[PDB]
Image (cartoon, rainbow over the protein chains, first blue to last red):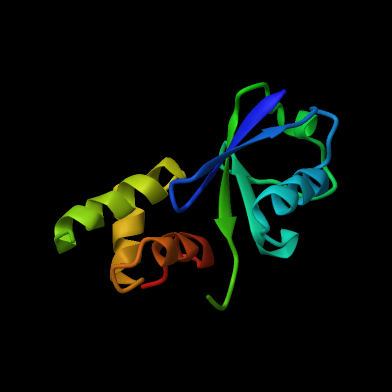
Length: 76
Length: 49
């Protein structure tokens, strides 16, 4: 299923995932395609911060949903 | 090149969609120095005062 990840710079990335994928997996796909280290990623959906060991189905994320990506960092 | 106000309400609106009313983020701007991203990272850490 396709999902959208909206970043704070107005870039939206599309990912192909399965509801059975874990949040850790999603973060690895984002690293693979945009290069952001998983440790800097904070994923938000329906006002909840997503936890690494849960799956997308745990949160009821359906096709064409948009997650928000906030970056955690102490540098530029 | 944009005025202070404009970008201001634009911070709100962005961080807004992020479940952060214009007031929490704008006040977060008062606490972020006018920054948006920091405004929300602020929305996070909390809203002391």
